[PDB]
Length: 211
Image (cartoon, rainbow, N blue to C red; front, side):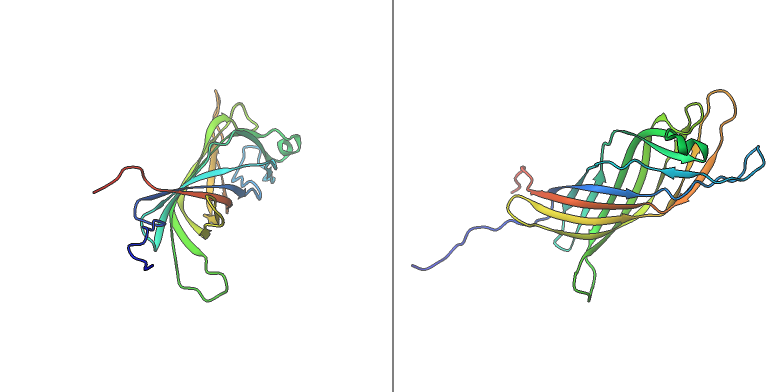
């Protein structure tokens, strides 16, 4: 008739592992930034990216009930984007693979507004695969790396299916160079890329049992 010694509860414990899978929408590409050129003139170029479906996978590690860690990663295929004056019009300027590598932790913070989202921060490195960039003879692009900040919320809506939504911000400038034979052209462009992650996640508890 009476109740005693209830069942154990396990929802969040230090060392928890939850896979958060969501689509990351990158937003960058305003206009190239040429410093100088042998030609003498100082024209302006234009970059463009192809609109297509894309997904991203990140690993969230629950260590504390106040904060946690998340690592954004993805193995996208080879994509071709524009980035020039006359070459842009053609449609074939640069083509390579995407190597999005970001790792930051999420933490809560005081708030007054309705929604009480969380803010994170860490190291966000963006690299690519040397395939065929630039309108020149197999041109390469100098990747970049720097600290980024995350902003969003994470909850569990439904059974065996959680939800996650945040955004990654980190303004930086990429470089471009490479040439087979003659002297390559070292260029640089400063832009503020905006990544939007939206999808679901899945919580999981370690298998190894401790005393």
